[PDB]
Amino acid sequence: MLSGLNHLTLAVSQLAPSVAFYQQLLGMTLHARWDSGAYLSCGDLWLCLSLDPQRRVTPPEESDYTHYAFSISEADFASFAARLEAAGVAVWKLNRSEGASHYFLDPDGHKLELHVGSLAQRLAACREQPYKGMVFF
Amino acid sequence: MLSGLNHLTLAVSQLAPSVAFYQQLLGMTLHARWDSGAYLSCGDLWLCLSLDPQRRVTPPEESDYTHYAFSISEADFASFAARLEAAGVAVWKLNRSEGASHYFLDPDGHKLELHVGSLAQRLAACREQPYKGMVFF
Ligand SMILES: CCNC(=O)CSc1nnc(C(C)C)o1
Ligand SMILES: [Mn+2]
Ligand SMILES: [Mn+2]
């Protein structure tokens, strides 16, 4: 029986600028770095950055909607999004609205998101404005 | 301050086979579905499947090392891997490190992993036998 996410591994093209992005800009905790990777944490999340020469920097218009969202509180959301914009972090666009979210790209074009709210809150919101064809179990 | 992973969204080419894989084969809980997506949970992980015409069924040789690992106990590991093998699920890598890992593909070629063990256990192993260039913080 599966119990949750054990770790998320992102392939990166250059290790140093990616470590700087996740640690210095996003504030994640750096535990270890070596010649081909780094281990960080964000609360319960174990994030691994893995140096991969096959990673290409892809424009958001030509990558799919696969994305990774991080939790932030209502009180910090707007000021954090503002800090990312002031630092020149690029944005991307999703096809639909899923609540209070800010969409931004990492240096390799991984699609990231800041989101306020839990799954339970999302389901309650969707009961009032559902997506087309929505069924609840 | 970010507090953890809020949700993981995977782009899928066909909703029905992906729901079948995550819900029925992997045992995640289906909370809702709509014409272009579904919400599931696996422990404290909120997983979104998003139907995306841009998603290609991607062979493992054509994608980078980005991958998603799910937690499982050592006691359950071998029988879960055997279930995947009976269902015909492809493997994209052999485990060559210490620690139990099984590396398998979803129907669209997303790279998945079953892993036993935490970040703390990995850091302890690396302190005894560090990777090339490894520094701890
Ligand atoms: C499967 C259940 N887990 C999730 O809902 C992940 S996001 C999440 N979980 N708690 C929160 C707080 C912001 C209330 O946010
Ligand atoms: Mn999202
Ligand atoms: Mn892994």
Image (spheres, coloured by chain):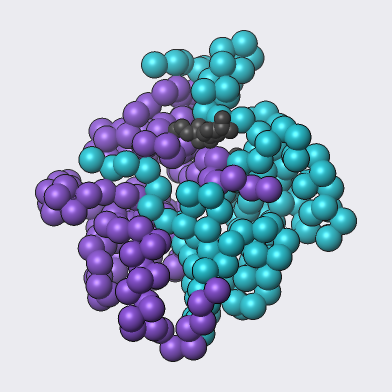
Chain colours: A cyan, B purple
Above or below residue B60? Residue B136 is below
Above or below — where is B133 with respect to A56? below
Nearest the viewer among A7 and A62 is A7
Q: Is residue B28 left or right of residue B67?
A: left
- Residue A63, how many percent across, how many down? 60, 55
Quarter of the image where one finds residue A124: top right
Question: Which residue ends up furthest to the bottom in the rendered image?
Answer: B132
Q: Residue furthest right?
A: A86
Q: How many marks?
A: 0
Query: Residue at horizontal 39%, vertical 16%?
Result: A137
Is residue B100 visible in the rendered structure shown here? Answer: yes
Say if residue B50 shows up in the picture: no
Query: What residue do we see at 38% from left, 78% from top?
Result: B127
Q: Position of residue B58 (x, y in %)?
A: 42, 59
Residue B114, percent from left and from top: 29, 55
For the residue pair B84 and B96, the one nearer the viewer reads as B96
- List x then y, in percent, for residue B94: 24, 70
Q: Which quadrant would the N terminus of chain A be assigned to in this image? A: top left
Asked whether, in this view, residue B99 is left or right of residue A51, the answer is: left
At horizontal 63% and vertical 53% (from top left) the residue drawn is A111
- Left or right? Give the position of A44 relative to B20: right
Q: Residue at x 40, y 33 (%)?
A: B41
